[PDB]
Image 1: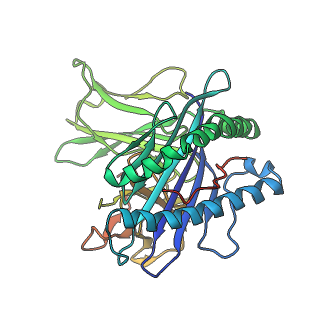
Image 2: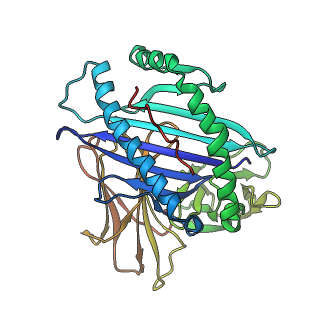
Length: 273
Length: 97
Length: 12
């Protein structure tokens, strides 16, 4: 699919007065590559993968400056939003932002997005056209109004169409070894004589990249997918992901059941039994 | 408020006596204030915590992970404290799930 | 070259 460059900002107000915790994380596709946290003294934007270390000092200095200024911005924003909702200064609140860009086939912006949320719920969002805003309530309409009068959508759109896509292409080039590779899942079926004369078959897919995958159990003689126990896709800890799907069959029907695995790292869908 | 989902698992298929990696993946929770600890026979293990992030529905997720060597004796689990849980949620590790 | 340089922001 199309490659992605995404940023996730979390600002958490504290009842202990004035500051707020600010955390920023940056992803290329499903690979985290930078982080920022204002909790530690002398805080810096820091690498989280080897390839981004190819960048020089000036890069890290500029990124650190920008995220620190953004942090102070979100600190002020928490108080502004608290005011809008007529909430007390007693409780802690959160302001989240996700933004980023997808690379099209011509090396240009395919889709760009920017979205802000207050205490877990949609606050304001930039529209597909990248020129207008969707406020989710009346408090956000004040923000929508301010932004509309200051042509904020223009700068957001010029960032997404310009700097974002070019740095995404740059990052795809710096880590082409690992970023442009699809890693297929290592699959296997384990058998557990567990239930009362019922056999649990569990189909495992391990170490696949990117996130998206399809795991189903099919029964010879029926077309739809069979009911199963399916856990959510989970990180392996090394940048890959894993998943499994299990079901219990009578203790004689082991090879009447097939696990089907669909992943973009596989040349063709996979069948295990 | 949204309660955390908790998964405890090894990075590689667990083999007795063989070095591996133990993960506690906590997702889908809000507010972001949460305590996550990995436990070996009830005692806290020293482990790394990922940087706070969140999914497309704004719910947060964290990963707590550390090196470990499973055997047939030591018991592993993960304990999570969150405002939505009246008691700390403890999930035992199992090589099969 | 990666984060939006916000100036004139503290503007919600």
